[PDB]
Image: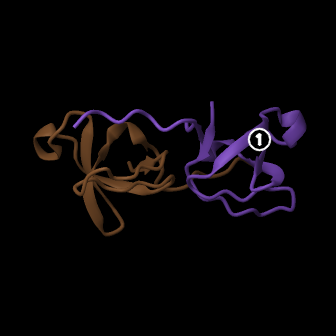
Chain colours: A brown, B purple
């Protein structure tokens, strides 16, 4: 299972992670005790680690599906 | 109501539309009569119109969500 950013997000604080549409986001914690806020998760995109709004990602992506026949 | 590509799709036919993950895809028809094959939809990306595998897109996109409070 992977998560994919479905929207761009621009940090309004230094501990926040920028998201761009289509980014694969590695979800490192869903626990508010770590993100510091309900509805914020901790993740990584490329080399960057920070918190991001959980409603900006969708569980989806990974291996591309086999396309239907033509 | 927006559709987003969740995976990259490399065309393998002259009427096929390339997708890149995170692209918004304007869906012009879901009808196989139009696409010419079940599970292939017709759409527009980047000014080009062609067909793509319907299993590469997800309904979602539109406006970025309201982020939760910190």
Front one among B18 and A68: B18
Residue A28 placed where, x, y %?
23, 52
Residue located 69% across and 45% down the image: B25
Extreme residue in the bottom direction: A47
Q: Is residue B63 above or below residue A69?
A: above
Q: Which residue is mark 1?
A: B41
Front one among A39 and A12: A12
Residue A55 visible within the image: yes
| B39 displayed left or right of A45 | right
Residue A70 visible within the image: no
Residue A23 figure quarter: bottom left
Extreme residue in the front direction: A12
Residue located 14% across and 42% down the image: A36
Q: Is residue A15 above or below residue B70?
A: below
Residue B15 placed where, x, y %?
86, 56
Chain designation of label 1:
B
| B27 displayed left or right of A5 | right
Dot 1 falls on a residue whose secondary structure is strand
Residue A49 placed where, x, y %?
26, 61
Residue A41 figure quarter: top left
């Amino acid at each position: 299972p992977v998560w994919t950013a479905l929207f761009d997000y621009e940090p309004s604080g230094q501990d926040e992670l920028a998201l761009r549409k289509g980014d694969r986001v590695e979800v490192l914690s869903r626990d508010a005790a770590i993100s510091g806020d309900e509805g914020w998760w901790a993740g990584q995109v490329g080399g960057q680690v920070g918190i991001f709004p959980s409603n900006y990602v969708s569980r989806g992506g990974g291996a591309p599906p086999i396309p239907p026949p033509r």
